[PDB]
Each structure stands twice: as structure tokens, then as C-alpha cells.
Image 1 (cartoon, protein in one colour):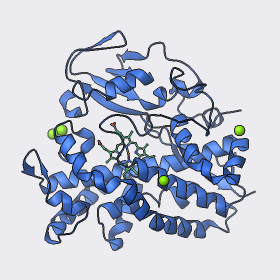
Image 2: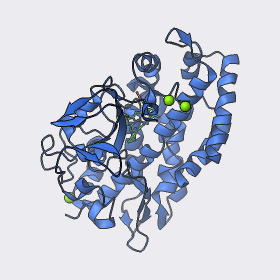
Image 3: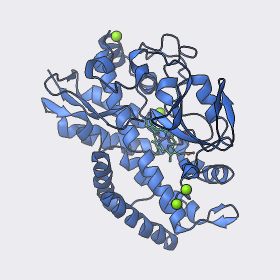
Image 4: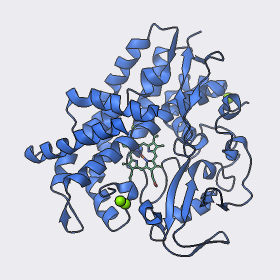
Length: 370
Ligand code: HEM
Ligand SMILES: [Mg+2]
Ligand SMILES: [Mg+2]
Ligand SMILES: [Mg+2]
Ligand SMILES: [Mg+2]
């Protein structure tokens, strides 16, 4: 069966998408001036040692409040403080709103013969969750819909969004409430109250981290359903397969193909000697194709497994929006299949993908009913 990668030429440089093995699981590149980690076990080792493999990228050369760029102990405190807003409890509380939105979005395309799934369902979806968590007024949510689209399209839309979030942080200081913003106002990291800049960077981080990759998740999954008809038929007849389907979609096409790490000391990984102050690229996409961990990794199999892929990552930085992303993917797919009995890709209007080399996901997906 022809994979999505072979059908449309998804990231030809991503050799693992075409069943090709890396010569070594840890390889240095002179052109990139960075170490590449391709193996599953080696990835877990790198991700499991944040003291050696820092997340603070500025070391190799503003980021305060941004969890992605923060190491322990500051990371430990800041994550612990915001953890409550990402639990399965918050997932269940937000589901009816996202369900309603999914219905509304699919009402618009219900009678269409052709439609782009990305612009119809995938793009106008993920903002709502983050907007709810950041207590963005419902009237200002359209602004974030526009801003996030522009940044995806390509500095100017980012400037306006940061400008809004600065005043939003100052407004929430005048309005005390038991939400995520309110807890950030009363928060203490390193024995110090977080300034507006800390909260702005956190808000910016959350918006970026909760948008494009969720969009890629929706796109990639439908792309996989179109490539595997026998498996897609089982999904329509058994909707309880959807959670497993989404997990495999992330293994097969990891929206975040790689994350970045920086060495703090001389370290040996898989016999390779890494020097201090060097960039390390941890390829989630490559690690998800490791046959030492996954049986027949070249095959798409929704029935895995359990499926311990690295699409959400691994370690202390493990995706906080993990539970929220799976839910958003589930609701989007379930209702999409309910509304459209038949969905097909168009050879005349082929799907396009994000150019980013550290990503693997759909940018546009034209669909037809017959
Ligand atoms: C399917 C879509 C998604 C993908 C591909 C994805 C990818 C990731 C990955 C791989 C990490 C770990 C990063 C690392 O180790 O360096 C992560 C953490 C994070 N994610 Fe998820 N994610 C997704 C959904 C979300 C959602 C729904 C949110 C929230 C709205 C979110 C916001 C974050 C934030 C703020 C972090 C940083 C947490 C930390 O550093 O402790 N991402 N995202
Ligand atoms: Mg910095
Ligand atoms: Mg700086
Ligand atoms: Mg099949
Ligand atoms: Mg769920």
C-alpha cells in the first residue's frame, strides 16, 4: 500500500519516511553545525537529561516565562503552577464548546462538493482552547484567528499580538479571578513574582504551541485515512478507533519532526563524543520509525499498541496540551466522518505541506465528496 509520503512527496530529505535507515543513530553534520539524533533510545536519553541537554537555546549564541526555553529549577516551578489548566478535567469542561464549534464549522461546508479541509475545519479550530485558557474575551478571539493565520502563511502580525497580550496581562491584574491568568499574577518563580513580560512570553508560547501542530494533526490523519481505505472503513464503522488512529498519525507523520537541545558539558551518546556548547537536534519523526521500538515501523497501523511515539515528546517538557490535542483531534474527525459519508483527495488539486524542515504536516488539503 502506497504511503502518503510516496503519494505526494512529503519531505524527501526525511529519509525515515521512505523506510531508509540512518547510518548511525547519532550523527554530526558540518553543514548544519549540529548533532542529529535519529534513534528512539538515544532520543529518550537526551530528553531524559535536561541538565546536560539544555532547552535554553540562547546558550549557543525575552525567553523568561517560556517553558520551552526554560530549564529546571525555574521550569519545575512554572510547569507545576500551570499544570492544573491542562488536566483531563479541563479537557472535559471544554469539550462541549469545541464540539459546538466543530458542528458550526462543518455546517458551512455540509452542502459543498469540494472544500479545503484546512481552511474549513483545521485552521479555525485550535485558537478557541488556548483563548479559553488565557481568558481572552470572546470578542477579541477573531484577532487571534487572523494573527495565527498570518504567521502560518509566512514579524508584523506577531508585533500586534504581543502588543495585545501586554495590555491583556495588565488588565488581568485589575480583574482578579481564579483562572490561569490569575494564578500567573499571584505566581512565584525563583522566590519572585512574575512580571508582565513573563506572562506575555508564556501566553505567546501557549498560542504558538497549541495552534499549528494541532492543525497538522487533523490534516495528517485525514491524509492517512485517504491512503489506507480498509483501515478508514473500520474507523467509520467503529469510532472508538479514532484515539488510536490519531496516535499512529503522530507516529507516522510527527507534526514536530524535531526539537532542539544544547549541550552543557562533554557527553557521550551511543559511542559518539559530543562537545560542550553544541546544538543537538532530536528527531521525533526519525525516532518514531525506529524498528528497535516499533514492529514494522514503515507500516501505518491504527491498532497500536500501546503506541509510545514521541509526537508529544518525552521528559520534563512533555506536551502539556497532550490531553487537549487528542480531544480536539477526536472531535474534529468524528464529526467530519458524520457529516461526509465519502471523502477523497483530488489529483488535480494536490495537498500541500509546511516548508519547515523540522516539521511534517499538511498545509492545505482539498477534498471532494464524489
Ligand atoms: C498535535 C499537536 C501538537 C504537537 C505536534 C505538539 C508538540 C509538542 C512537543 C513535541 C512538546 C515537547 C517539546 C520539547 O520537549 O521540547 C510540546 C510541549 C508544549 N506544548 Fe504541545 N503539541 C501539540 C499540541 C499542543 C496543544 C493543544 C497545546 C496547548 C494549547 C500545546 C502547547 C505546548 C506548550 C506551551 C509546551 C511547552 C511545555 C514545556 O516546555 O514544559 N501543544 N508540544
Ligand atoms: Mg534566552
Ligand atoms: Mg536576549
Ligand atoms: Mg488499509
Ligand atoms: Mg480525549
